[PDB]
Length: 195
Length: 195
Ligand SMILES: Cn1ccc2cc(N)ccc21
Ligand SMILES: Cn1ccc2cc(N)ccc21
Image 1 (cartoon, helix red, strand yellow):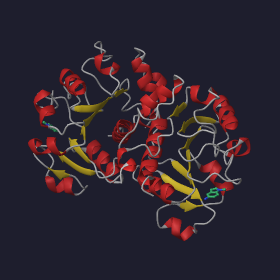
Image 2 (image 1 turned 60 degrees about the vertical axis):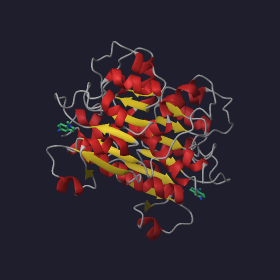
Image 3 (image 1 turned 90 degrees about the vertical axis):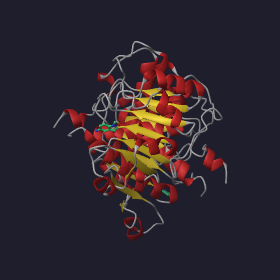
């Protein structure tokens, strides 16, 4: 609540990082390389962002990404479509969301219904090259499924602030060239800490 | 013109990268580490962003960063203050700008007046801990001065897409822990390439 904006900002930063590969570019540059072709990226303007979970953080993500000309769609079983309309998010059933999304971001608790919200069945229904963000709770994105999706190219990149186990003991995601990551920094700001 | 949104989008990415140290955090995770204290960051909401150069790219940065609640101030020799106000940028003489800014971003051409726009004189007029972005042209930020300001703490972080020499021959800037960088990727998007 006091940390909604810290979470929402981190999420939007991860979205920009997946579009432009800024973390990977910095690593390259620090290793003395000048790799222009490798880090050809994409524009956010005109892309579709799916927001799973339309509480405080999700809404704050939406209105920030709207300023980039992203089309913002989403799903929340609790929040009315009239409330989500108020902040520019079209609610759609999940089955409709997957095929539309260039980017998908998750803003849910960890429940039975949301553990593996993104899993092999839902990755399959996504547009090829979807990019995924999890700054919410470890386990919302099935980590096995995500790796399989990165391996095939069904998922073109992922940004993870949270893991099923913290620190993650399985390193295959964190080591993947298309994965950007942080050690659960969503609420690690001077402001969130200090009310 | 085509490439203005690519540049503006990178610049905003750089700004969020600087606020939450996302490239350094990924590098630390990739080094097998879980260092959360080290990467305590800052909220963008409420902070002041100084934009030097209020052209197309500068405007586009402003309206995106306005959605994060950033106060947007700036300077441009040509653009009148009532026109900048119409896109949310409060124009002030440079002398007024330096002490006010949490972040500064340059969007100027490279001219005698803008080469070393940021230099030892102007850095010492800044607020301690200012964060700086150059996705415009190498040399607008004097690189020697920026290094000294990073070494003292007067500058808390910088994000560079461009260098006085490309690739950079001098390495101290790129190698600094608080500097994030890319190999001149501001126009390197599929969309910008394609027309
Ligand atoms: C299955 N699922 C998808 C989004 C979402 C949000 C909440 N609050 C609960 C469950 C959810
Ligand atoms: C000295 N200076 C500061 C900002 C700026 C913009 C332009 N286009 C030219 C010169 C400038």
